[PDB]
Structure formats: structure tokens, C-alpha cells
Amino acid sequence: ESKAELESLAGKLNPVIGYWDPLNLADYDQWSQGQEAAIGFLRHAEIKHGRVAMAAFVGYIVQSNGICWPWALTGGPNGVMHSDILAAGGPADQWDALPTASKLQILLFVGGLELWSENSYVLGLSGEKHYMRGGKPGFFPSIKKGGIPHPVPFDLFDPFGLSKNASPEKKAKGLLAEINNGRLAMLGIMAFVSESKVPGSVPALAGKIAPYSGEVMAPFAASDNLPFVADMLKSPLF
Amino acid sequence: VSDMEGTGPETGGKVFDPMGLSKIASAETLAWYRAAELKHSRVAMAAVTGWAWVSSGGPLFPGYLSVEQGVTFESLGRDGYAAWAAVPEAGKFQILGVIGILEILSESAVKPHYMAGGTPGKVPLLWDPLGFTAKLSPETLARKRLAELKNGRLAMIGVMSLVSAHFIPNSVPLLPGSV
Amino acid sequence: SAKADLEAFAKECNPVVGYWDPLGLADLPLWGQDQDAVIGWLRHSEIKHGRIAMAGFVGYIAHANGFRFGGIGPQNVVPEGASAPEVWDSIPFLAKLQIIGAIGVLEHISEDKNFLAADGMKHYMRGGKPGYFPTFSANVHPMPLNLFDPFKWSKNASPEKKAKGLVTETNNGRLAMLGLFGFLSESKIPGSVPALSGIIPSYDGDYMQPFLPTGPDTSLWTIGNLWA
Amino acid sequence: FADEFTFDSKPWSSSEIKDKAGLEALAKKLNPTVGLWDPLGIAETSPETIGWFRHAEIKHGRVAMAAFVGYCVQSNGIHFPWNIQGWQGTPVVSFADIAAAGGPADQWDALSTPAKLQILGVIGFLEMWSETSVVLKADGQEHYVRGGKPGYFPKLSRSDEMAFPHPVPLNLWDPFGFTSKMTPERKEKALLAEVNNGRLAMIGIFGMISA
Ligand SMILES: CC(=O)O[C@H]1CC(C)(C)C(=C=C/C(C)=C/C=C/C(C)=C/C=C/C=C(C)/C=C/C=C(\C)C(=O)C[C@@]23O[C@]2(C)C[C@@H](O)CC3(C)C)[C@](C)(O)C1
Ligand SMILES: CC(=O)O[C@H]1CC(C)(C)C(=C=C/C(C)=C/C=C/C(C)=C/C=C/C=C(C)/C=C/C=C(\C)C(=O)C[C@@]23O[C@]2(C)C[C@@H](O)CC3(C)C)[C@](C)(O)C1
Ligand code: KC2
Ligand code: KC2
Ligand code: KC2
Ligand code: KC2
Ligand code: KC2
Ligand SMILES: CC1=C(C#C/C(C)=C/C=C/C(C)=C/C=C/C=C(C)/C=C/C=C(C)/C=C/[C@@]23O[C@]2(C)C[C@@H](O)CC3(C)C)C(C)(C)C[C@H](O)C1
């Protein structure tokens, strides 16, 4: 995009404010590929943080209320039940109590999705380009059209085609709602985690978020026997 | 000096010469400066790589160093200075003498001399016996020469950090006090 | 003429006093450079001293009264209730070194030809604006915010208002200098600033020595403190 | 917004007071006896500073009269019949307990911390809705420092683009049109009154606090 279009989108997201860049991060040229590339990267970062944050907000609400799945997570005569992962503690403790294979495969599945989004050939095959090259800032390409060898049932966005045949006006309105909901949901999820780590940080939630001891920004806990994990966790931090 | 290579985005496209040593440098003096820089950079790259491999824990040379006199590659130890102290004086003299022969061949054999209008750092034998950097175009070759200069400048600072950690103990962080 | 500009600036600073140079430093030939370059130097020095003295006064109120950031940092070795001369004395030696080094890097960027030329300016002794810190538009790694006006609150301000702001900068910097050394002087010659009698505690130790006492040699890094 | 965050002056385009003569006119209109009583000489200032002082006086009048009436009611002991806490599994506190805490300062002190934060948050929301230039210009006025009427609270109920995501029922000032239509200058009479009883309530509330 350009700064003018970014200002217009800000006006459409909140006409009272309009553009709000106190740091002038849009003019901050990072990656040395022009203001258009920088604004594209920032827009994608906002959209992706928002998507992950709203998803994690719903996940935190669902997991913190004792709504584990009925089926099991590990397989064998001694397998970690999802109920055991629930009983591990609060949601962050559930993640830390996951098996190492579960953690690795979750994060690597997400990584596969991320590189799939970042590749320009698949984006061009699905239409549009990389978000730093004029494409739509936040747009996951089609795992079907990319040409993976086996035919996948569904794409990641809109698997059942419910937003299909949407009005273009509804599409723009939906993207505005996506950005704003993500903007608020980032604060929501970080407020949950901040209440978990520092009690009383978010005054409204008092006694309603379980405590947590380990670092939340540490995907692998002490149970994860992998290279350097224990040495990394040896020294803690606020 | 502005048209001598080695400048990059790290300086900002300009020459890094605050003390003004380039002002008092002629063409021959500038060629000498570049030749010394290239030699020191290459030596420091080799020295850092060797010291890091030896001290880090990499698989060092199998077998004996001296069958008679009973000195072994494993027995020499992983401290760099202690290893260079315990290696035989014959071996030290041999390394130094071969390096000296190569230095004198670099000085004399390359007849268009880097001081007398030649390319600094053009040691003819000791480069690319397998011909890897033979088909590279001038642009990528200049890029790689700048890479040589940058990497080796970093290597010089690295090896001086190593010897500072060995001499002035607890001097550099990320170097255990012994060495 | 640079002298004429300086006299007009003094009249703007205070028309009652006007140009007040009892020593003729504006006519001194510092380094043998001409009067324009010397006046550039003196104006830069005045503005720099005033700026740092204003920051020093605000930081004296911050440290002595008690105003600290939370978390792991240099703040956790300074004893509580320590006075403003003991805070700098009590921070780690690396903290003192890196503070002075960062200030040095900012000085270097302030006087570097690269940044001042990228901003379309010249050195303050070579026909430039005395007291101008350039944007970091020539630093190797693209830099988020500049030193002066980081949020660009003065992107659209009148040149007359900017001139009046510089007139304010000089005067307030002079007054801040006087106040800050009032604080320093009351601790090493008591009864010298009558108002501060009983407020500023005495301090036994050379102010002008930066690295004395050297302070603790603690290692405050936690995650990945391999250098310890 | 970043283009308007100037920290400086822009030319005025209204009939609002921007000089000592204009201040004197309003001074005699408020009270022909005293006139302009400006020993500190804060009439000898810029238009923006004059508007700032005018709005500050008006806002102190609002808060002081509200404080005086609240002080009188809370001293009378006309408490609310509700419970002030204890519905989301929290301890139970009653307005009767807040009243029995002590005098109105003690009552505010006995008020729970998040209750204080929420009240101050609402007041801050009102303050910044007042200060929002874009809202006033969607409405019919500007910021008081830049030539706007000092004291205008913008409407919180609206259907414009600058309207809240959820509809708001009523506005802060005149929710049910109790002003309806005063005459085009009886509004100004009421403004003069507001300034006078605002000053009187200012003196009254500080005197009561001192007592
Ligand atoms: C905080 C703090 O204090 O940190 C401390 C810790 C820390 C950071 C560790 C420190 C250090 C030391 C450092 C970082 C030292 C760095 C050393 C460095 C940078 C060392 C380069 C060697 C390069 C070599 C041998 C290359 C050979 C390469 C060769 C033979 C070739 O190029 C060949 C070839 O490529 C061509 C040309 C053509 C291509 O067709 C391919 C081929 C293969 C044919 C310090 C200074 O103490 C500071
Ligand atoms: C070194 C070390 O360890 O340090 C320690 C010590 C230290 C530093 C003290 C620590 C701390 C404390 C910290 C850093 C605390 C930070 C707290 C923080 C950051 C608190 C923000 C609240 C923001 C709110 C409520 C915003 C609401 C905003 C709202 C209502 C909106 O979103 C509105 C809106 O945007 C939408 C949704 C989008 C648009 O449609 C419309 C607009 C724009 C209007 C740590 C963590 O302990 C670490
Ligand atoms: C992020 C999403 C995700 C994807 C896309 C994905 C795809 C595939 C594919 C196809 C490409 C195969 C063929 C496959 C196979 C197995 N998965 Mg797997 N998987 C994902 C997630 C998890 C999690 C969280 C766990 C898990 C597991 C297992 C076990 C072993 C079970 C056991 O221990 O009996 C087997 C055989 C569990 C485990 O323990 O893995 C060692 C476990 O917790 N998977 N998985
Ligand atoms: C955690 C995941 C996630 C969440 C929770 C979430 C929520 C919301 C909300 C609710 C607040 C709204 C209202 C909304 C609306 C739209 N989303 Mg969306 N979304 C998520 C993920 C993705 C991805 C991966 C894509 C995407 C898209 C679109 C389009 C398509 C417009 C078009 O076809 O032009 C519209 C209208 C696709 C796209 O192309 O966006 C440019 C696309 O790739 N979304 N999205
Ligand atoms: C701690 C340090 C510090 C303090 C305490 C301080 C206080 C004040 C005060 C308060 C009494 C006023 C009123 C004032 C005014 C101006 N300051 Mg100043 N200032 C400090 C630092 C810097 C730096 C780094 C720069 C700078 C500048 C300007 C310009 C020029 C604008 C222009 O001409 O564009 C104006 C008008 C920039 C410049 O170019 O100065 C020649 C510049 O780089 N200031 N400054
Ligand atoms: C404005 C000034 C300023 C700047 C611009 C700046 C820049 C950089 C950069 C540049 C990219 C790096 C890479 C870097 C690295 C480290 N800084 Mg540093 N730093 C500044 C200030 C301080 C202070 C006050 C302290 C400090 C420290 C450390 C430690 C060691 C921690 C430890 O050993 O526990 C490390 C590794 C602390 C310290 O040494 O504590 C004993 C400490 O207190 N720094 N710092
Ligand atoms: C609790 C707080 C509070 C109190 C105690 C209080 C008392 C009195 C009294 C005393 C008996 C009178 C006689 C009076 C009169 C007027 N008040 Mg007032 N008032 C309060 C609050 C507000 C707010 C928020 C606004 C406001 C206004 C007006 C207008 C203008 C109407 C117009 O011309 O539109 C008139 C005539 C609006 C305005 O624009 O004020 C400049 C406006 O926004 N008032 N007000
Ligand atoms: C604890 C818990 C639960 C819960 C809960 C829930 C849902 C709690 C909800 C609480 C809620 C919803 C609390 C609102 C307060 C609103 C206030 C004080 C508004 C004041 C508003 C005021 C003073 C407005 C004034 C005016 O508007 C007036 C009148 C007219 C306008 O012209 C002018 C203005 C704007 C000034 C469950 C669901 C039971 C189970 C769960 O497991 C845990």
C-alpha cells in the first residue's frame, strides 16, 4: 500500500481518530525495500497478530473453563489424556505439560502454514502477490491450488465456502472488522497472560485467571528433553 | 584511497580513516596498507578458526605428532597457548620456515609487485588449487573480495579478543577466564 | 556577521542585558579559526551545556527524591534512600561505561559529516546551525526514531517559533546550569546556596571523576549470562 | 490528527473573547460592580491562553457546584438503597456502609478501589470526548483554545460517522430538553449565572473542605 491508503483505512477503522502512528513506523523504513514494502509488512504483522490473538483468546477461555476434549492426546497403554493435560494446571501449564512431540508438531504445522503463506509462487498461483510486493496484506493462499501431491479436502480460509459469493463491500467491511477485533484481542490475550504471571496487573480479572510460574514466552518446558532446553530454562526472568 | 575497495555499508559508503593515515599515503603506501590488511585478515581468519576448533571440542587430529619423543595430538591439550608451548620446537621452526618460504615466494615470484604497481594480496600458489573461483564474473569476485576483507577484519578482532582473554584474564566477555 | 547574529540573539535572550561578553570569548581565536567558526563553537557549547544541565536537574529530582524503573537493571544495586551523588556511584561500572559510551556515540553522530550532510546541514563551525543534532538517516542499520523530536511534534512549526524556542533553550539552559551546580556546590561547600541549607546532603567524593568509586561489578543479566 | 498536534497557534475565526476588551465586556456582564479584576494580568495573553482560562474557570464551576451539592447530600445522609458490590462472587458492601464510614471524604475513602477507578475512567472519557476537536467539528464548534465556546460538551447520542458502535440513549447536558428553547440570549444569561454561582460554589466547597 501507500501512506495515503493506510490513512484512508485508518479513517475507515475509526473515523474519529483516522491515522494513529505516533512512532511514524510507516515512515520507518525497515528491510530497505521502500515505504510500500514496509507498510505491507506492518499490515500483515497487525493482521496476523490479530488473528492469532483472537484465536488464542477463545482457546484460553475454552481451556481455562475445563472444556478439554473427550479423546486422548498421546497413544499407548500409558498415554497423556487431554484430561491430564487439563489437570496439569492453568492453560499455560497445560501447554507446558503437553508432550514434546505435541509441542513440536503444533509449532511446525504452524510453521508450514507460515512458509506456505510467505512463498510467492503459491501466492501468484492463487492470485495476488507477496504482501510487501503489492499483494493483499493479509491473505493465506490456497493449499489446494498450490498443487500439493495429494488432494486436500479443504483450504485454510473458508473451508466450507460460507463467505463464498460475498459482496465486495462486505469483504472490505469484514477486513476492517478483522483488524479492529484483532487489535482488541491482542490486549485481551496479553491481559490474560499478564494476570496469570503478575497478579493484580489487570484489575478487573482478580482471582479468575490461574497462576503460572514458568515463562509464558518459552514454548518448551523442563519436560521437553531437546538440545539446550534445560540449559535455557536454568536461569529464569521476570 | 576512495577507489581502493573495502568500503561498504558498515562505514556508510565512505572510507574509515579518522586519524588521516590515508592522507599521508601515496599509491605505493596505500598498496602496502591494503596488502598488510589482506595478509593480516587471512592470518586472523585461519587463527580464529583453528583456535575455535581446537578449544571448542571438535575432533582433533588422530594419531601421533612425534612417534619418537612421545608427543600426541590428544596429549597437546585444547588450550591454544599451551598447545603451541607443548608442540616440539622442531615443529614450530618448521611451520615458521615454511611460512617464511611462502612469504618470500609471494614477494619475489609475483613479478609485478603490489608496491611496484600490482595487485595487493595475490599470493599465486596458495589460492584455489581446485579452480573453484575460476568462472566467477568480476562483479561477484569483487563482492567476494570485499567479503574476505570484512570477515578477516572481524577475525583480527576475534583473535585479539582471544589473546586478551588469555593474557589479561576475565577481559573479554564470552571467553572463559583461562583462555 | 556571526558576531552581529550573536548580539541580536543576546538581545532576544534578554533586551535589558543584551550582549554580555565580559571576556571577549566571541573574539577569542580558538584553534586559530575565524570569528564565525569560534562563535559557532561557543554557541554549540552553550546550548550543549544548557541541554545537559536541564536534563541533569530533572534527573537530580528523579534520583534523589526516588524515581526508578522496575525489573532487572542497574536500579537494583543502588541502595534505597541513596542520594543523587550516590546513585551514579552505586550503579555498576558497566552501566557507567555504557552510559558515557552511548552519550559519546550521540556526540559522534552529532559532529559526523555523514549524518549532517545526509540531513543537508554542515558542521556548526563550518556555516551550520549551532546546536543541531542530525537525524539518523546515514546510520548503517535503519533507525526507528531520531533524537530531536522523535515523534515529530514540530514537523510543522513556524521558523519564528523555532527561533523563539532556541532563545528559550539558551536562557533555560543557563538557569538550569546555575541550579544544577547549586545542588553540587551545596554538598562540597555548605552554606553556599542559602535556600538549599539542610536539603542537599554532604558528599565526600570527587564529582568530576566519573569512575570513582568504580561501583559494584555485578552481572545483572539472567537469561544467557554465559559471561560470568 | 498528527497534522493538528502542532503545540502552537493557528488563527482564530470566531467571536469568542481573545483580548482584554472582550474580557472586560464579559466581566461587566457577569457583574457590573467588580468589572475585570485581574491583578496577575492574565488577560495580557494570547487568544488560546484566554480561551484556556475561560474553559478552566467554567469546568471548575461545573465540578465545584456538583461537589457542593454532593457534599450537602452526603452530609444529610441520603444514601442509596442498593448494594455497591457482591454480584460476581465478591464481598458485599452497601451504600449504607459507605455512609456510616464517616464524612463524605471518609465515604470516598471507604469506596472500593476499582469503583474509584471506574468513576475516574468515566470522568476521563467525558473529558476526552470534550477535548476531541473532530467531534466538535462534526458538531458545530471547535476546541475552546482554538476559537470554540468554552464549556460545550459534545453530544454523546448521534448517528453520524463519528458515532459510537452501539447507540447511546441520551447526552450529558440537557438529556430531555429541559433547556428546550431558551431565547437566543437567555442562554447567555444562564451562562453568566453559571459563571457566578460557579465561583460562589467554588468558594463554598473549598470552605466546607477546610472546615
Ligand atoms: C560480547 C563479546 O565480547 O563477545 C566476544 C565473543 C565473540 C563474538 C565470539 C568474539 C569473537 C570472535 C569472532 C566473532 C571472530 C570471527 C572470526 C571470523 C569472521 C573468521 C573467519 C574465517 C574464515 C575462513 C577460514 C574462511 C575460509 C574460506 C575459504 C577457504 C573460501 O572462501 C573458499 C571459497 O569461498 C570461495 C572464495 C569461493 C567459493 O566458490 C567457495 C569456496 C569454498 C571455494 C569477540 C571479539 O571476542 C567478542
Ligand atoms: C526488565 C523487566 O523485567 O522489567 C519488568 C518491570 C516492568 C517493565 C515494570 C514490567 C511491567 C509492566 C508493563 C510493561 C505494563 C504494561 C501495560 C500495558 C501495555 C497496558 C496497556 C493497556 C491498554 C489499554 C487498556 C488499551 C485499551 C484500548 C482500547 C479500548 C482499544 O483498543 C480501542 C481501539 O484500538 C481499537 C480496538 C481499534 C480501533 O477500532 C479503535 C481504537 C483505536 C480506539 C514487567 C513486565 O514486569 C517487566
Ligand atoms: C499440528 C497438527 C498436527 C498435524 C498436521 C499432524 C499430522 C500427522 C500426520 C500427517 C502428516 C501423521 C502421519 C501423524 C502421526 C502421528 N501424530 Mg500428529 N499431527 C499433528 C499434531 C499432533 C499432536 C499434538 C500429536 C500427534 C501425535 C501423533 C502420533 C503419535 C501418537 C502416539 O504417541 O501414540 C502419530 C503416529 C501425538 C504424539 O505423541 O506424537 C508423537 C500427539 O500428541 N500429532 N500426525
Ligand atoms: C484466526 C483466524 C482468523 C480469524 C479469527 C478471522 C476473523 C475474521 C473476522 C472476525 C472478527 C472477520 C469479520 C473476518 C473477515 C474476513 N477474513 Mg478473516 N479471520 C482469520 C483468518 C483469515 C485468513 C487467513 C483470511 C481471512 C480473510 C478474510 C476475509 C476475506 C476477504 C476477501 O475475500 O477479500 C474477510 C472478509 C481472507 C482474506 O483474503 O483477507 C484479506 C484470508 O486470507 N481471515 N475475519
Ligand atoms: C536534554 C536536552 C534538551 C533540552 C532540555 C531541550 C530544551 C529545549 C527547550 C526548553 C526550554 C526549548 C524551548 C527547546 C527548543 C528547541 N530545541 Mg531543544 N532541548 C534539548 C535537546 C535538543 C536537541 C538534541 C535539539 C533541540 C533542538 C531544538 C530546537 C530547534 C528546532 C529547529 O530549528 O528545527 C528548538 C526550537 C534541535 C535543533 O536543531 O536545535 C538547534 C535539536 O536537534 N533540542 N529545546
Ligand atoms: C544508553 C545506553 C546503552 C546503550 C545504547 C546500550 C547498548 C547496548 C548494545 C548495543 C547494541 C548491546 C549489545 C548491549 C549489551 C549489554 N548491555 Mg548495554 N547499553 C546501554 C546501557 C546499559 C546499561 C546501563 C547496562 C547495559 C548492560 C548490558 C549488558 C550486560 C549485562 C550483564 O552483564 O549483566 C549487555 C550484554 C548492563 C550491564 O553491563 O550490567 C552489569 C547494564 O546494567 N547497557 N548494550
Ligand atoms: C454538573 C455539572 C453542571 C452544572 C452544575 C451546571 C449548572 C448550570 C447552571 C446553574 C444553575 C446554569 C444556569 C447552567 C447553564 C448552562 N449550562 Mg451548565 N452545568 C453543568 C454542566 C454543563 C455541561 C456539560 C454543559 C453545560 C452547558 C450550559 C449552557 C449552555 C447551553 C448552550 O448554549 O448550548 C447553559 C446555558 C453547555 C455549554 O455549552 O456550556 C458552555 C454544556 O455543554 N452545563 N449550567
Ligand atoms: C461474575 C460472573 C458473571 C457475570 C457477569 C456480568 C455479565 C456482569 C455485568 C456487569 C455489568 C453489565 C455492569 C455494568 C455497569 C454499568 C454502569 C455502572 C453504568 C453507568 C452508567 C452511567 C452512570 C450513565 C450515565 C448516562 O447514561 C445516562 C444515564 C444518560 C446519558 O444521556 C448520559 C450518561 C452517559 C452520563 C456470571 C455471568 C454470572 C458468571 C461468570 O462465571 C462470572
Image (cartoon, rainbow, N blue to C red):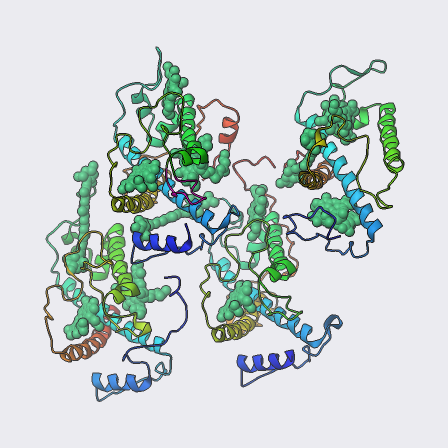
For the question of whether residue C144 can be seen, the reply is: yes
Q: Quadrant of residue C100?
A: bottom right
Q: Residue at x 39, y 40 (%)?
A: A128
Q: Is residue B6 or residue D71 the one in the foreground?
A: B6
Q: Residue at x 80, y 37 (%)?
A: B122
Q: Indicate the position of residue C132 as horizontal and vertical percent values.
A: 58, 66
Q: Residue furthest top?
A: A77
Q: Residue at x 52, y 28 (%)?
A: A231
Q: Is residue C53 or residue C93 the one in the foreground?
A: C53
Q: Is residue B179 shown left or right of residue C167?
A: right
Q: Indicate the position of residue B56 as horizontal and vertical percent values.
A: 66, 27
Inspect the magenta stretch and tell me whether residue D71 lies in it: no
Q: Residue furthest bottom?
A: D33
Q: Is residue B161 or residue C4 the one in the foreground?
A: C4
Q: Indicate the position of residue C31 as horizontal and vertical percent values.
A: 74, 70
Q: Quadrant of residue B149?
A: top right
Magenta-colored span: A128-139
Q: Is residue B116 shown left or right of residue C111?
A: right
Compared with C140, D194 (above or below) is below
Compared with D107, A218 (above or below) is above
Inspect the magenta stretch and tell me whether residue A136 lies in it: yes
Q: Quadrant of residue C21?
A: bottom right
Compared with D14, D113 (above or below) is above
Q: Is residue B102 shown left or right of residue A36?
A: right
Q: Indicate the position of residue D175 as horizontal and vertical percent values.
A: 13, 63
Magenta: main secondary structure: loop
